[PDB]
Amino acid sequence: ALDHANKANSEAQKTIKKYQQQLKDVQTALEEEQRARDDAREQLGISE
Amino acid sequence: ALDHANKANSEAQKTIKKYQQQLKDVQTALEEEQRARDDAREQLGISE
């Protein structure tokens, strides 16, 4: 029972590390795109 | 051991849910900007 359980937690906590990598680069995908609005609005400030 | 094992998997099952909510609302922010950056270009297109 324990060997089934102790392996199940390691397969569980493997997903824990798997998510926070995917949360990590999505945060970078914001930091590109949030900055990508900023010049794009500034590009309106040149054109208008 | 076993009750202290299965308690950890619940704390594993809670902590995997904490990021599961945290990945959803930041995704909306990416869906927030992506139509907002679209609001820049369609404004830029009628300008340029």
Image (cartoon, coloured by chain):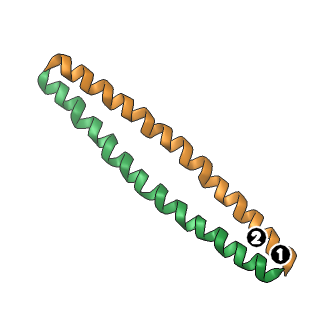
Chain colours: A green, B orange
Chain letter of the residue carrying label 1: B
Label 1 SS: helix
| Residue B6 appears left or right of A29 | right
> Which quadrant of the figure contains the C terminus of chain A?
top left
The answer to whether the residues at label 1 and label 2 have Cβ atoms under 8 Å apart is: yes
The residue that appears at 24% across and 29% down in the rendered structure is A41
Q: Is residue A26 above or below residue A10?
A: above
Quarter of the figure with residue A43: top left
Q: Amino acid at mark 2?
A: Ala
Vertical placement of residue A18 versus B23, above or below: below
Q: Provide residue B7's location: percent of width, then percent of height.
A: 81, 69
Location of the N terminus of chain A (image quadrant): bottom right
Q: Which mark is residue B8?
A: 2
Q: What's the residue at 85%, 78% (across, down)? A: B2
Q: Amino acid at mark 1?
A: His
Identify residue for label 1: B4
Q: Is residue B1 left or right of residue A26?
A: right
State the residue at coordinates (32%, 24%): B39
